[PDB]
Image: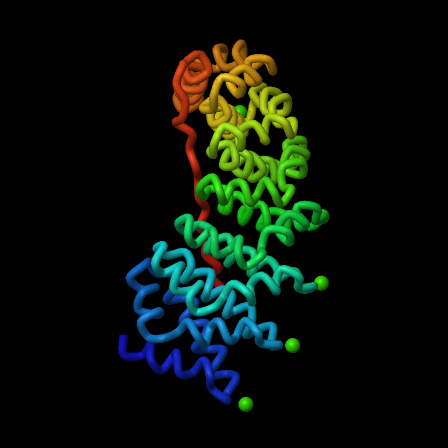
Length: 300
Ligand SMILES: [Ca+2]
Ligand SMILES: [Ca+2]
Ligand SMILES: [Ca+2]
Ligand SMILES: [Ca+2]
Ligand SMILES: [Ca+2]
Ligand SMILES: [Ca+2]
């Protein structure tokens, strides 16, 4: 309430101490849920925060990113307000920053925007984010790689046209290569990304198959890691939701025997996901694939 208008005014303060302070307070208020986010938007914060993405002051920039990321953790309409204030061109340009901290925070903000509805996701694609995000799949910096993977995964949680944009940007070969990663964080994310691409139409599922995902996905059905096991099951289950050619590719890769054995796993969630995937492979229908979105905060 009554202190918020002052905080927003202070985003243009000639006193850098007052500015940085107001920015941090807004960032923190935007951690408090969608009603609190809406109070920040209603006080007029957005134009100023977006303007500050052009700041050459790295402390200001990092906090502005933090604030906008938190606002973009809200509802689809709150995300759309951020897009409407003009955030995307600045965020996309920041994907080329040589500052790893700024890059990380930019990625998180983009990822949150791409956790909105299909129209919000399409704005991200139309702003040109995908070629940069796909290029970052090759980063030797695990932190950067992890945040780019989340952004791609969220973009692939849209409709078939959004998924097709991801495929056409050349993401699949890198994502399939990541299924070999010894890094459990990266592996999990690569599986989210591929699962979401495999939640589209049959020709999207087939692009995943044609890029060579199945043998690695079937190997992961041998993991003692219950989290990785569930993630590989989700991916196989999405692919098995396609048509006959897709179901048949899954059978040719040897999944049947393993899916059947996994119905005897003590973990009830694994049991259930195995049974469901198996029923789809032997079913005559299609559909039932699952999409997942990730939202993250930034509390400084
Ligand atoms: Ca001054
Ligand atoms: Ca500077
Ligand atoms: Ca650097
Ligand atoms: Ca490294
Ligand atoms: Ca490891
Ligand atoms: Ca285990």
